[PDB]
Image (cartoon, rainbow, N blue to C red; front, side, top):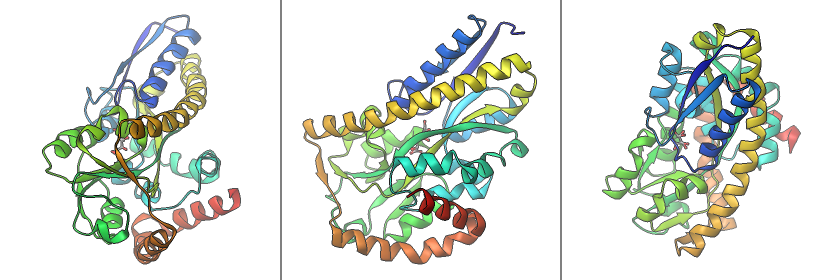
Length: 310
Ligand SMILES: O=C(O)[C@H](O)[C@@H](O)[C@H](O)[C@H](O)CO
């Protein structure tokens, strides 16, 4: 019980990013599972606007499918702000376990009230600081840096707390802000830094891995609800296939991105053990302060699930 249908899937990252390629994989599996009747059309590189517009497109129904970072969802469902807290997850295995577990599900379950279906979580990843003013090797080096952040009170508060001038901006305006030096820097996973070419305008990279961002793989509830059960199954089955593909592609892409950026002679720094503990001490107080704007129960439940998986 599948009728011919065309499905639009916009997103912000470049087409050849790992998640870009995972979106093409989703389209192929949807085709395969529906004998070519359900055709997904991918619009990468922000062609359908940034996360915030994609989100609104799905709620209204001009778009069907997207993936977005959790941070712009905090603007709808504040509990999603939890993932902008630094150092939540020690590694990708913990993140997978927590996100695929009850604490991840509790958050996804809040989406239908806002007109969205959270099909599952994909991996954006560990974020790393890039900038064009000077090497960042010490907490103090962040002082006064004009750093773009995702558009969220948690992201803004965290980096202001670390001494930056935190400048919320949509991802889709970021390359130009970096190139014109309207902003000194940004922070994102390595494969994004690479595939969106931020290295061409960011001579300095710090391997800080300070925050882990999930993507949410989203469907418009208005559109999803009008589908037949056989059609919903194609989408959810393809979503499960594509999550596994995405996460594997993301992790390989991280390894490849690091190699490329080093071989291309980007200047790479890290936070020493001493600097890392200075970071944590600065971080504790308004992590504590920010629980009230996220949701105490979400924060404590995520932190507990992460301990149990680690
Ligand atoms: O810096 C950001 O805002 C995110 O890290 C990007 O991954 C966006 O979510 C993009 O729109 C996803 O395609």
